[PDB]
Each structure stands twice: as C-alpha cells, then as structure tokens.
Amino acid sequence: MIQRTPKIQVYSRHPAENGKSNFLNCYVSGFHPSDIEVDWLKNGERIEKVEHSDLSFSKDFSFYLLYYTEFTPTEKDEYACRVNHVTLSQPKIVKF
Ligand code: NA
C-alpha cells in the first residue's frame, strides 16, 4: 500500500496559437491514491469556472492532474487552487 501527498503548482500560460487567451493552471503532481478534490477560489470565495482536467499516471502509480481554466486576471484579484486529498489533514490552498 502507498500514499503520496500531491505537489501543487499554480501558474498562468497563454496558448501560443491564441496569445490573447490566458489560462490559470493548477498542476497537481505525484499523488496516490487518485481520489482527489480540486477547485478554484477568488479572493477566498469559490468561483464558478468552466472546468478542464487532464489526468494521467506513471509506472510507480503516481497520478498527475492538470486542472485548468481560462481567466482574465487583475492585479488586485487573488486567485488560488484548493486541493483536498487523503494525505492532507486540511485542504491545501495554493495562491497564483
Ligand atoms: Na484530507
């Protein structure tokens, strides 16, 4: 049996084929088991966004999730990714 806590990375990318678009990304990497909850916050409040995820796994059965959504960020607005996993006693919130 094995359990591994996720690493969580929050960053923005513009797709090069549509430079004007901007995506908020939450890369949740190396975790086990695969059971997980991930959502978006803004200024602390959950926000309704259109959800996209890519889920894959490696040979040692770690899971990797890219959770991403388009956004138009402000300087004053605080975006964060919130992750709940069996290894985390509290939800982990990672600011953009
Ligand atoms: Na937990």
Image: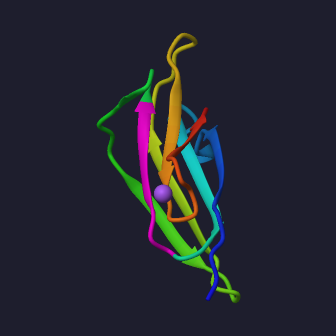
Q: Choose between 23 and 48: the one closer to the eye.
A: 48
Q: Give the left or right position of residue 20, taking residue 31 as reference.
A: left
| Image quarter of residue 70 | top left
Q: Which quadrant would the C terminus be assigned to in this image?
A: top right
Count of residue discs: 0
Q: Return the x and y of residue 64 as percentages of the image width and height.
A: 60, 68
Identity of the residue drawn at 50% across and 16% down: 77
Q: Residue furthest top?
A: 76
Q: Give how far across and how far down residue 72 sits, in percent.
A: 46, 25
**Magenta span includes 47:** no
Residue 95 on image: x %, y %: 60, 32
> Can you say whether 63 is above or below 23 in the image?
below
Between residue 7 and residue 85, name the one nearer to us. 85
Identify the residue at horizontal 54%, vertical 10% (top origin). Answer: 76
The residue under the point 45% across, 64% down is 36
At 64% from the left and 63% from the top, the residue drawn is: 5
Percent from the top left, x then y, of residue 63? 59, 74
On-image quarter of the N terminus: bottom right
Q: Residue furthest front?
A: 89
Look at the picture and state if 10 lies above or below 73: below
- The majority secondary structure of the magenta stretch comes to strand
What's the coloring here?
Answer: rainbow
Residues in magenta? Answer: 34-41
Q: Is residue 60 above or below residue 87?
A: below
Compare residues 5 and 23 and report the one nearer the observer.
Answer: 5
